[PDB]
Length: 100
Length: 100
Image (cartoon, rainbow over all chains, first blue to last red; front, side, top):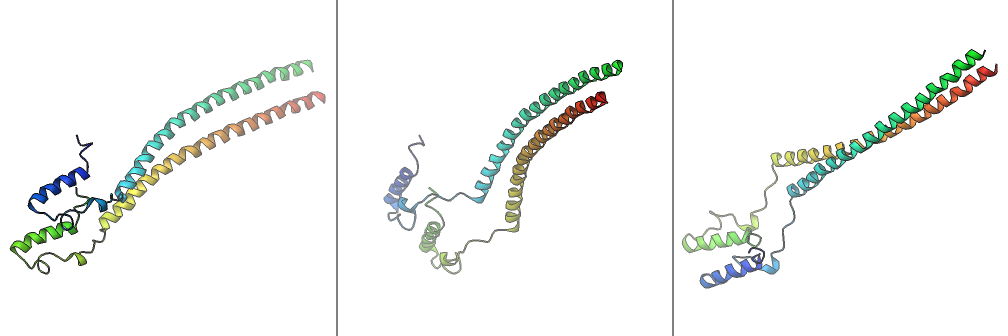
């Protein structure tokens, strides 16, 4: 039931309570709701947010690293096959030699 | 309800309380709000802030490291293809040889 029972409700309530026994709560006891402006986030809150954001980034990075490594492996195997074609080139070498 | 119930409110309250039983709180009991100037941060607080800031920096650094390594891998594969072009150069060598 909290979702309804937030801040304003609470202040009203408490006040009423007070208003039954100690009346003039407004201005010595409990800051009036019109001025109970929400607090600024702390440096501790902010730095932990940006650092916990980085601590998930890195994971994105690790995942993406695997993709790249895979690409590189495939490309290496392709260059292997090109150099095997250079070996096929040798054939011509030996045959020119046998021709002379 | 704390957001309203901060410091001033508390002092007023407590005072009142006191003022009912022990009156002259102002100047022997509870420092007057006009002079209750906020405390300076400790060396322990400061050093932990700057060290917890560095402990997220490093993560930024690790993430950025992956980008660089990737760049380098790609460049290596490119140089591989340039040297494969030098192998294509050999062709001309063997053919000049067959010409002579």
